[PDB]
Image 1 (cartoon, chains in turn orange, blue):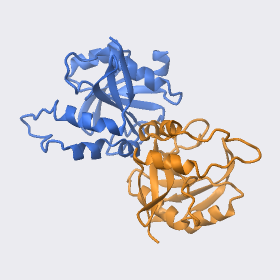
Image 2: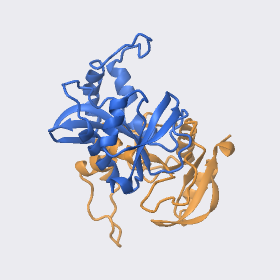
Image 3: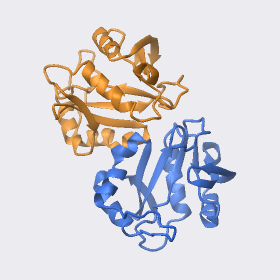
Image 4: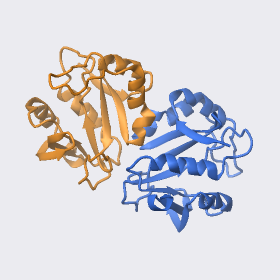
Length: 173
Length: 173
């Protein structure tokens, strides 16, 4: 049980494309529809395109095996209505939504979160990590808390209410 | 005649490597030194690595042929002491130092500048483009002025004084 992260590179885009075609669920209410093409993936996840939005892509690995995709982003200046009240350039948010996109039968839980937190605090410009799980996602909230995150309350995002959680460098230590 | 820019991808790293061992000048005051390997270049300019620093890499093209490399960056929050007085997330900096690195002949002047500015302003989050040429570089400064930038004065950077120049979305229109 060794969970670790690396930068995602373009060679990973084929793999991500494969994983998104595993994770593809059309719910009865039917957003989604499409189902991504290799070109769709390249277009959305190209590292250079993510760079324009201050997003950094990662591959989460279990025992050297890539099992999912993660992203960190600079909260401040995110746009499309995201994190509009942010003031501090050092806040990084994390997006673990694709962190089991390979559909392993078990999630890397707080181990995954700790490794991402540790990696991000390696950059001296980073002051605090935030994450915004669904208010109904009690298990993810608990995993974040076990990893050192503290619930701050519920915020309205473009995707709806979210439970806003943070870990400062100081708290992390 | 027709200058365009596209996002740089990993495929371009070899070409960039070649351009760099091509426009390679060692100055009497010694620096630059080591001389770049493919590995140095692929490591330093890997788009995912640039993403971690909120830097977007571009390949400048003339009539569909690659002639040089350009980067833009989010000024706010850059660190290593860069742009510490910035407060606006919408500010993007440009770095044209390698924009004629193919050294295939005559340089794209204002045309290049305008195309990079246009591309950045296509992002609604971008409020202002900045550039920081050497104060002795009177010709670069003139090209930036022809392209719509306005001198704001001289600022101290980690690399010494630079002439601070900007073009607001308003001014560009």
